[PDB]
Amino acid sequence: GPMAWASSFDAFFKNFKRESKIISEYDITLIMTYIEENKLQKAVSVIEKVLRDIESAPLHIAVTGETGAGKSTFINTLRGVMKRTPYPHPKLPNVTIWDLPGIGTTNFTPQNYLTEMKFGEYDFFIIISATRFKENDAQLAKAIAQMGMNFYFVRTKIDSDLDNEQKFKPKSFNKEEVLKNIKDYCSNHLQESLDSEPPVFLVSNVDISKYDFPKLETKLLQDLPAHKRHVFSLSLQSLTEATINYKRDSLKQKVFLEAMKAGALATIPLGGMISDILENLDETFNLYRSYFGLDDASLENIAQDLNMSVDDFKVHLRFPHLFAEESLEDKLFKYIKHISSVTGGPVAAVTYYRMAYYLQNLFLDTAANDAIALLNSKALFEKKVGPYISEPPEYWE
């Protein structure tokens, strides 16, 4: 009883990368304590409080740097698009990317710049440069860290410098040597002023899949408070498998907690059929489609590149057909048996909410696999219908 539901709870959250956990290990420890003491109502009120903090958590990101750093293109690419300027995210009103003028552009000291730019409103600072980070940049970072906050040095316009070098020396172009020289110069000069060797993230302003942008996103996740990881995961653009999987895992944890909130303690059965639960979940499912870029509007462009209609293209995606007919409820019985033999399942006494949980979990895993397929839509289809059953040799194809 009590001891077994705490182990399922523990075993569920053990399955996730450390930087993706939306509750802290203290939260988990508290919740497990109450479950083990047979205080499930107390455990539920903790989960409710956690979920309220998660759902209302705002995200304010300060991007500080000079105008030559392409700050505008950087900010638009984050959002999928002497005074600070806000740029709300187009899909998430509670996310705001702020354009902060370069400290060198102003004439403030670091401490005065921070107070002028309202440093307490932000979750972290991005210090951006298209060139090298000056000693004033290092002084700013030092102040930010003294305020107990986080900063990240981002060197942008990497694609422009590689292009110039490539056109300069087409036959001896060494991509990795350019990157190493750029990063080392930036690192070595920040190390002299700053107490520790700060990481420097090399990025393209127009393509967040490239260079160090993936490692940046992982470090930002890892440094944020646990409850802020969900809204930050949602704010990412679903353009890499890692980013898609960050969203998948964050939403899977959230629906697990929602299941316990709604169904750990309810006891008169709600009744209905699986078809009724699915009807009730229809708007939730559409919200999930929107998180993953699977809504009809987003699927139009991709279907065109494949000379298909959205209806055609959706034949080859799994989420539309997940529930059909071998009956559905037998498929679900076996699914539940598989999962709950492994991680115990959700803490949900109410069948309605137990099944809502599994239906949402399944939809989330499917939507994420579909989104991953969208990254390489044409090639996947062309390989699928074409004859070859195996992968091509390395540099031939």
Image: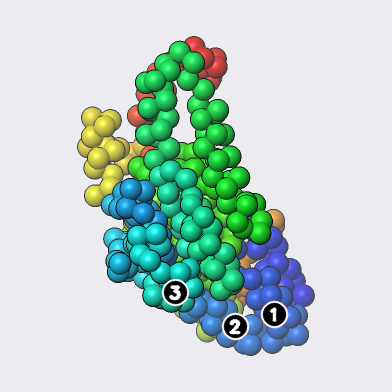
Q: Which residue is mark 1?
A: 30
Q: Secondary structure at mark 3?
A: helix
* Residue 108, numbered label: none
Q: Secondary structure at mark 1?
A: helix
Give the residue at x 49% y 43%.
Answer: 202
Quadrant where the image shows the N terminus: bottom right
In the image, taking residue 146 as reference, residue 207 lies left or right, namely left
Instruction: Give the CA separation, mark 2 to mark 1.
Output: 8 Å
* Residue 112, numbered label: 3
The answer to whether 193 is drawn above or below residue 5 in the figure is above
Instruction: Give the CA separation, mark 2 to mark 3.
Output: 40 Å
192 vs 168, nearest the viewer: 192
Which of marks 3 and 1 precedes in the sequence? 1
* Amino acid at the residue labelled 1: Leu
Nearer mark to the viewer, of 1 and 3: 3
Specify few, some or many for label 3: CA neighbours under 10 Å numbering under 14, 14-19, or 20 or more.
Answer: few
Instruction: Give the CA separation, mark 1 to mark 3.
Output: 41 Å
Specify few, some or many for label 1: CA neighbours under 10 Å numbering under 14, 14-19, or 20 or more.
Answer: some
Residue at the far front: name it: 107
Query: Where is residue 180 drawn, in percent x and y?
Result: 57, 34
Confirm whether residue 273 shows in the render: no
Q: Which residue is mark 2?
A: 46
